[PDB]
Length: 106
Length: 105
Length: 106
Image (cartoon, rainbow over all chains, first blue to last red):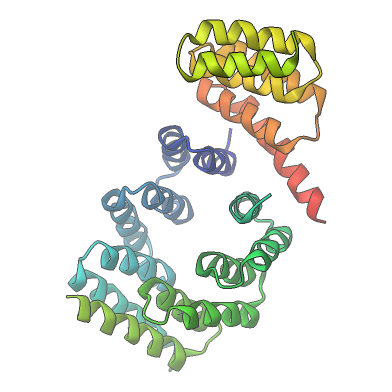
């Protein structure tokens, strides 16, 4: 009945091994607001948890696109890309994160 | 109860934004096995979520120390450090992760 | 007609044989101790796996009403409801369970 409740429900479903249903509900949560970076990150984390790494990368990329100066999102995307063997992209986003950290340092 | 079930309870709480109690459950889970990097990382992130940045960095440093060449762990530590304004450290570990990715390539 | 007998038999039937007969003897086991939440739980699980969702939900609701402070029972009920399409009810019972988990800490 709300984004948060559908997300938590999806999480509970995932814990009990109900992968398909979990993804279904998490996708509903995203559908209520497709531009919510938090929900997108949650869905990407669920998809990655269920071995669907490419979709996870897709939604992480969208989350990045919505706010590209987000060090955390960049790092997560980079880790996912690295795990899947996409070295150049991973190093790219990690270097972006480094650049932002540098900006904060100065 | 087991480490897995404790972690599940803790995550159910963490998803609700209830970091304070979730940290209690995760502390139990970590107590059952102090060298589990998964549980250590989860506890660290929960502590950062609650607002205990330095202690989070501590547990993350332990997680790193147990398996120093792990890209995910390194990146996570880098993020936690960057959140606390410790730029040089963060960039250092991030660069370490980068070099590992490059080595794998 | 002991509970050990009935459960041994039901398990023997479900493990390799008819799910229906196993359900029969699980019903017998439940009738033996209607306040036994483990028997109700097993019955609900078997009924669910056989495709009898509403019935599973019935016995799980019964189990819940038998011990309202049981986290596992509430979680499983919420799972069955969410799987059945009842998102509001499921979210309600998840909320009860989570409230219990939280209270058990603080």
